[PDB]
Image (spheres, grey):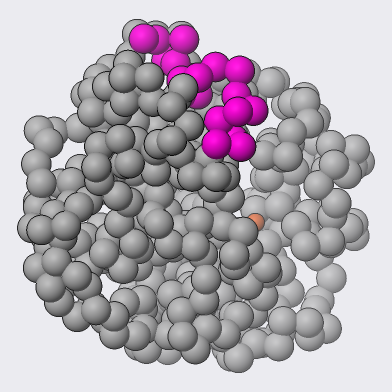
Amino acid sequence: YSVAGAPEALALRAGPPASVRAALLAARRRTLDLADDFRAALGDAYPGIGYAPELNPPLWELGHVAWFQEWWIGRNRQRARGVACEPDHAREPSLLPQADAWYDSGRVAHRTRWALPLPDAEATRDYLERTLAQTLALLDELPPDAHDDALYFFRLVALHEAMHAEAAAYMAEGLGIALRELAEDAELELPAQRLRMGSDAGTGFAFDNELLSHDVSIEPLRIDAQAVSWARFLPFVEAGGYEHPAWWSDAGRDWLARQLLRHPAHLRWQQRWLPLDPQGAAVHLNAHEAEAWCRWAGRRLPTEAEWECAALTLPGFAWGRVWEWTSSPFEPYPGFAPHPYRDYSAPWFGTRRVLRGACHATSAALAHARYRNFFEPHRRDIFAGFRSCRAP
Ligand SMILES: [Fe+3]
C-alpha cells in the first residue's frame, strides 16, 4: 500500500507533539482566513444568513470551534486516557459561562443557533485565541515520545477544526460568498486481492468509524483514474438522462420528480455565474445523480472497499478534487465502538452514504484514503462528485 495521504495527514495522525502543534496553528490560520472571507461578505452581522438545515451562522461556527477545542483539551480532566476517556466526566468551567448552552452541537437545537446572545466577532476571536493559547501550553507539556493516548485529543480537535473549515467553504459556496483560498481520462485495472480495510491499531489516530481494520475480498474491476468530469457527465444530461426515470433508483425517481430544473445544481452551460469548464470534476451531484449516470454509462459506483483498495495500490489513481459517492451505506466496520466524541459516527449509520477521497476545500492534514465521509444521499451543497468502475 501507498501512504494514505499527504505528509501533513500522516504527521497529524502519527507524529509527535511538534507535528500536532504545527497542525493546530495551520488549522487556526485557515479558520481565521475563512472567517475573514465571511467578514468581507457579511461584515460580522450575526446571524448574517437566513435559516437552512445545511447552514449554521458563521459566528456560531467560530465559537463552536473554540468550544470543542476547550471541551476536549483544557476542560478535559482525562486527556491522557485518549479513547478510554469517560466522555461525561465533571469538567472545569469554560472561559464563557454560557459556552455549553451556546456551542455544544449535541445540546443546542439547530434553529436556536440563529437566536443566541453570542459574543460579537471580536469577543469570539478573543475566545478562539485564549483557548488555543491554553491548548498549545498543555501540548508543550508532552514529551517527544508521547503515546497515541496522550496525543489523542490534540489530534481530534485539529481534525474537528479542519472539518468546520471545509464546511465554511461549502456553506460559503451555497450562500454565493467568494473565498481567497482534471488531467487526461484513463481506466485502471484493479486485480483480485485481499484489502486490509480501515485503520490498523498503532498507525496513530483513527476515527472510530475506521475500526476495526479487517480483511475484505476485492473483486477484479476497471476503475476511472480520476473523478467524472463535466465533459464525461454532461452527455448523460444531453441524452435526456434527467427525464428517463428508468436510469434512477426508487429514491432517485422520488428526488428527480421533486426537481424544478432537470439538470445539475449550479448549471444555468454556466456555473455558480461563469461559463462551465468541461475539464473540471463534476461537483454538487448527489448519490442519485451519480448512480443514474452510472446506469446510463453501463458502469457503477465503487464500494468504499474497492475505492480504498484502488487509492492505496494504483499509482495512476488520482483523487482529492471532489468527494466521491460510493455504493456503500455508512455502517460500522466489524468491532466498531464509539470513541469519546460519541455522536461523531454512531447516530448517522444507515441514513448516510459513504463518500471517499477529499475535495479542494479539504485540509491536507485531514484528506486520507481510510477516511469515511458520510452524508445523506440527497445532499448537493457538499463538494461531491464521483468516479465509476465496471467488471474486468
Ligand atoms: Fe463540530
Q: Residue furthest front?
A: 246
Percent from the top left, x then y, of residue 328?
43, 62
In screen coordinates, is 379 left or right of 362?
A: right
The one nearer the camera, 67 or 113, is 113
Percent from the top left, x then y, of residue 382?
51, 39
In the figure, residue 15 lies in which quadrant? bottom left
Task: Identify the magenta region.
Answer: 253-271
The one nearer the camera, 83 or 33, is 83
> In the image, what residue occupies the spot 83% across and 83% down?
90
The one nearer the camera, 313 or 144, is 313
Q: Say if residue 66 shows up in the picture.
A: yes
In screen coordinates, is 238 left or right of 209?
A: left
In the figure, residue 292 lies in which quadrant? top left
> In the image, what residue occupies the spot 62% across and 59% down?
351
> Which quadrant holds the N terminus?
bottom left
In screen coordinates, is 191 left or right of 93?
A: left
Percent from the top left, x then y, of residue 127?
72, 51
Task: Let me know if residue 266 is in the magenta part.
Answer: yes
- Where is ligand 1, by quadrant? bottom right
> Which quadrant holds the C terminus?
bottom left
Percent from the top left, x then y, of residue 81?
59, 90
Above-or-below relation of 365 to 232: below
